Amino acid sequence: AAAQVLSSVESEIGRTTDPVRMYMREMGTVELLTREGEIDIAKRIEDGINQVQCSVAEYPEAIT
Amino acid sequence: ETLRVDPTNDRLSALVEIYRMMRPGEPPTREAAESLFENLFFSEDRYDLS
């Protein structure tokens, strides 16, 4: 519900212009993900590029 | 009559508004505003009278 915080605070931001606050407020939205985010995201990347290397079969087009 | 215009009832909203005036644009977190309030006046390092 971090975008909801953006909603209210932006609703009464004190005419802020510093991008520092903006960037930190934005990156603080998405929280950390630890001890399985690493592995399951790697296995999703596995799934993607190995779906690719499966796609890499059978090229009459790319005969080279 | 000033109390009659006092919007708050709790400690926490007052602390929020203080944190707000001194750090606009950021959202509130309790311990931040608390340590801020106490260090402005009750920390020996950030305040001295001579």
Image (tube, coloured by chain):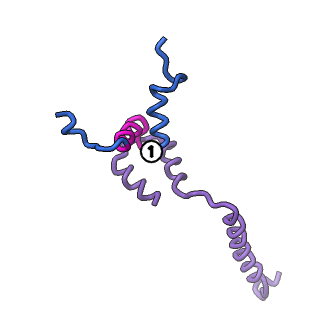
Q: Quadrant of residue A35?
A: bottom right
Question: What is the crowding at mark 1: few (fewer than 14 residues within 10 Å), some, or many (at least 20)?
Answer: many
Exactly how many numbered labels are in the figure? 1
Rendering colour (chain B): blue
Looking at the rendered structure, the secondary structure element under dot 1 is loop
Q: Can you give x and y, in whole percent of width and height, for residue A36 in the image?
A: 69, 66
Q: Can you give x and y, in whole percent of width and height, for residue A41 in the image?
A: 68, 68
Q: Residue at x 51, y 26 (%)?
A: B43
Magenta-span inclusion, residue A38: no
Magenta segment, prevailing SS (helix, strand or loop): helix
Q: Can you give x and y, in whole percent of width and height, for residue B6 in the image?
A: 24, 39
Q: Residue at x 54, y 52 (%)?
A: A27
Rendering colour (chain A): purple
Magenta-span inclusion, residue B18: yes
Q: Residue at x 42, y 44 (%)?
A: B25
Q: Which residues are magenta?
A: B12-25
- Which of B25 and A56 lies nearest the eye of the viewer? B25
Q: Is residue A58 above or below residue B36?
A: below
For disc 1, the marked residue is B26
Amino acid type at mark 1: Glu
The N terminus of chain B appears in which quarter of the rendering? top left
